[PDB]
Length: 296
Length: 290
Image 1 (cartoon, rainbow over the protein chains, first blue to last red):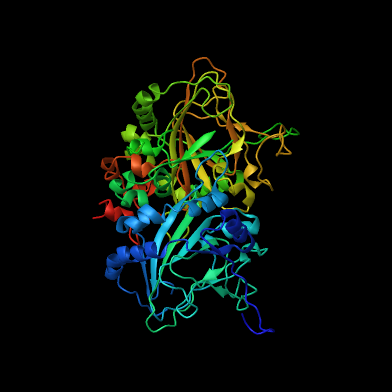
Image 2: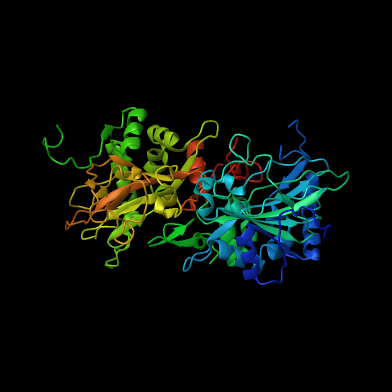
């Protein structure tokens, strides 16, 4: 708390992973983003960081003369690398309940799947990325405005601490409700230069859940020694294409050891949509693709 | 000229030979939302395709349900690559199809902006009820909310494998419905025009197709015949950002994938930055790049 008269920056609500999902969903609806403390346990986060570390050592640091991949290591093969990720982290019931509240329709099953599973290590000195919305990946989505449905949501987990100085993500709460969704540039955004943000200060295992409609951007890692790690669990709706071809690069040995909802998340199993007709997305001539892969 | 002077002029489908300019076909497609391409598939290849899928079509039982869904007295079959050499080696390698797909979907400097949604043999059986009027892009349920200012979602190259007649269940198209100001469900509750919606049959010979926008209202007609099984081949093509209805890269044998050109590998998801592999083309891991 600050002296009376100080300006108050935007509110980023926070809940323990033990709070009711409806009370966390309620804050997600208000602000577009919410911090879930203890989403991952400190021992699970430590084990995951250690389990992906040898792959992360082999990634070189990309340094360039301009970007968002400037001094940032990126690694997406978490299912292959980390048993704690594939056995425990993706199996968070709180994650899946919130995904259902966002994405799933009645009588249709899982309305969502994985877009990506990226580990990020932001090096000391890495610059701050432009303000943007994640749904800009699906370029038509902004044109539907705040009345549009959700494209994507992110559970952005802290693996090491997120501080203001080591570059914690800067969010714009309530930007999912602005009347018009433009790109954030001088030409297109009238608020440009005048958009107040709030960092997502978190401890390891905390995550923020962020709508694809919310304006955000990574902060500058101003430190001397802090290599800030994050795990982005990016989840899209059933009808959108994933940025990783998990079902073609994850081995069937790991597919056979997954639960049915994890197979669905990675495309080892289909989902049934109802269109006036029950339609399989990602199916096989009227059957679940899981039959053919030997998973039923 | 076309209609007797003074009469109401109904909707009509422009027709082009397959040797016409893709620019001339695409102008028609933009004006009306659909266009016939005569001879999209050659007579010899159409015949070889039908014969190659016939055993797959024979092992498909005929439902007689009266439940109003799209499978009542309608056979549907999506394993054309696996079943037909002519399909995978010849029919999908039409330069005109890709030139048209490139004008609908591709942006400069980003490669192919499209891939396959489905490859479906649709054989309407004698007696089949008419299907509901719909837009194909209702499969991506938010798209209608964007209106005619929205971008293109899906297009289908709907090819006649056997003749399409007014009497055997030819599709009834509503040209220009891609420009109506509000895209709603086509039913009594939601559509003010319901019951006063002008359609046209797509009359076609084996090898003809119509290219149709996902924004166009259409529906199969009733097969009033007693023996005419109206066989069609629907090549559905979507933006690269959208999920296919078939998991073609998990069901098509790698043996067939290695015989595809690069562009057909891309159509089926054997080649990729969507659908990638941790920063690299998935075709590397699959062993398809040399």
